[PDB]
Amino acid sequence: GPDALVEQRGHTLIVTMNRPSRRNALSGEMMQIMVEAWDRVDNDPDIRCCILTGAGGYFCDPSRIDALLKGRRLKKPLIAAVEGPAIAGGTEILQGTDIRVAAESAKFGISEAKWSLYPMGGSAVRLVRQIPYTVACDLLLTGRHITAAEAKEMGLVGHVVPDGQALTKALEIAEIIAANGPLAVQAILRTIRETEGMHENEAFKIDTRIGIEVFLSDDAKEGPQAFAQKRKPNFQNR
Amino acid sequence: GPDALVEQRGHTLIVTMNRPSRRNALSGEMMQIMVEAWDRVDNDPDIRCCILTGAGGYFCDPSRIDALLKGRRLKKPLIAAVEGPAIAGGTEILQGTDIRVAAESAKFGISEAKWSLYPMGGSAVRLVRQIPYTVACDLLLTGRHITAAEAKEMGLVGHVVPDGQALTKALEIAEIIAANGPLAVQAILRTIRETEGMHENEAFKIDTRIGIEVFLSDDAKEGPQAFAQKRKPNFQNR
Amino acid sequence: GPDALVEQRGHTLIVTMNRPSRRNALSGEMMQIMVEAWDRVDNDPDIRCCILTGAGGYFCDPSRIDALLKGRRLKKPLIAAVEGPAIAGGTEILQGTDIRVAAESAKFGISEAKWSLYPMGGSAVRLVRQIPYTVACDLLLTGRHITAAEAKEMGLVGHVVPDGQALTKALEIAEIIAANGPLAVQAILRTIRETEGMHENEAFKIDTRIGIEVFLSDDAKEGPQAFAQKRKPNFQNR
């Protein structure tokens, strides 16, 4: 089929990179479909969350590449579900996701330097910001590949599950996110984006300006009510 | 008694959030007493360190909230001693502390988004700066609660101790801090605050300007002397 | 011999701090030789990597101190190989290295505050950027010493090896770095340096400007060829 598969399942959009005979290596068609999917995530108020995964037991001016989430980030949470090889492109795009599940046999690495290529997916910026400095330097400069266990130990992913279970676990996480207040979830995400690189005192001013509107919503009344009643809240995104 | 308890024990001020019938939920009185305590920490040269804890087996424009250490940070080190539930407010204020002890059964989490509320204690700014990016996103966007062990594994706290021992461990740490050179301890803390969000080359200029005065002190002579004599230094904060 | 030893071994320069009767405590001569070595690393195109180690079973305006890599960073990767005590100066200079191997019995710590001294090697800036915030605060403010295992757990070093093996492991890592494309390795390193303290969207513009030239090189053609042929690439630094 198409080089990326796209399915809406309730409030979650699932995007599957889909060239399994080529280890889901990126194609022009794949990237075009991915950008259309990002647009749908950002613009459809019924979408509360997105999952990025790969088919067939694999995962996967040029300063802005929308498909690869470099210079663009989704306005709703993005969960990665990684099976198998995620070297090169896969580890780069992983860094543009927010919450991260790896199957036991998944493999990560940025090996561009081994072949005297430069990583075009933004790893030289992001990796030192997401895992400890020295480990990020080791991975980028040696091109060492790592296991899912090692990736979890260093904080590159948050969850490790048995092989074949990454997408199931990601769907569990998405169900939780979809059940949380979309106005609050999306406001938190915007603060995380906007306050990068600032002293915290400057950041708090933006944090408050972003967050205050959440309390005006019908959802901000229903939430505490549902909590008191020990039931699932019924949020309406307003 | 008062909604926050305050005791000076040698060079350490101990602040205990104290509404144990309400899981030490914040009150106006609690916050007023906390701000008075922060003032005392900053202004009393005899105070070298502060501990924030909760009673009864629990822990706990709006861009600046002094009581919650958002837009204000103590000029002397602040050690958290966390027993039991520290969800919501407790996990937020935890991020304004410097050194962190959790009892085995302590529980952390920022669950505001579950109820379509926004976290008003600055977590959307700080958490991604204090634990790995992906884990911070997971906690804030799902509202997942975590154990003390998990909190230690991700770097949210530094020490885990048996239940009922968090304050004892914190007092041990405070004794060490109180025995170190207050001029040096406080200078280090100021550099950490002031250099946030700068390239390191700009930061080193501030680091040196802050640190140089420490060497002019009587304490900077007594320290190396005491080291050579294998005795506890007698620092005078000058 | 000289207070720092310097050897070129193929594409790797090895710098050994060498006052083993004084636990490799820094001297004027040691620092002078170190700066000459940094110059050689930066300026000799045949050098692809550097190792900093200590002899004899030990490791080791003032806003810029070249010898201690404060306000200056090497243009090629720097790997630390730490045997034994690395307290004070050793832990500070460690933070200016990129990839880090510790022997089992190595000890780290910044104990200046214990003696009412200020750390002049830039730790008050860097440590909170390299390990989790709360752990960095604990180490700097208490002066607690840590084991190699603890250093690995917190992300201060990347590798732990048996005693006497730190330099051997570092040479293994250097062989890998030396075999990678120097143009790509060095470009990645420059992006990591230049993009510190910026929002990622500003950083990507610099990342791309730095990286694009790598693809014009003869090395960028030989790399993928060698990969396809399952052989070691023969890079020429052009």
Image (cartoon, coloured by chain):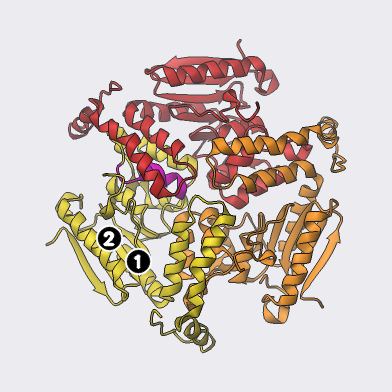
Chain colours: A orange, B red, C yellow
User: Residue C53 bears which disc, if any?
Assistant: 2
Dot 2 surroundings within 10 Å: few (below 14), some, or many (20 or more)? many
Quarter occupied by residue C232: bottom left
Is C56 situated above or below C231? Answer: above
Quadrant in which the C terminus of chain A appears: top right
Same chain shared by disc 2 and disc 1: yes
Residue C156 position in % (x across, y down): 42, 52
| Residue found at x 38% / y 26% | B175
Q: Pick out the residue farthest to the left.
A: C1
Magenta stretch: dominant secondary structure: helix
Q: Which residues are magenta?
A: C120-131
Q: CA distance from mark 2 to mark 1?
A: 9 Å
User: Residue A7 bears which disc, if any?
Assistant: none
Is A106 situated above or below A133? Answer: below
Residue B129 position in % (x across, y down): 55, 45
- Please state which amino acid type lies under the numbered disc 1: Ala
Q: Is residue C125 magenta?
A: yes
What is the count of numbered marks? 2
- Residue nearest the viewer, comparing B120 with A107: B120
Q: Element type at marker 1?
A: helix
The residue that disc 1 covers is C170
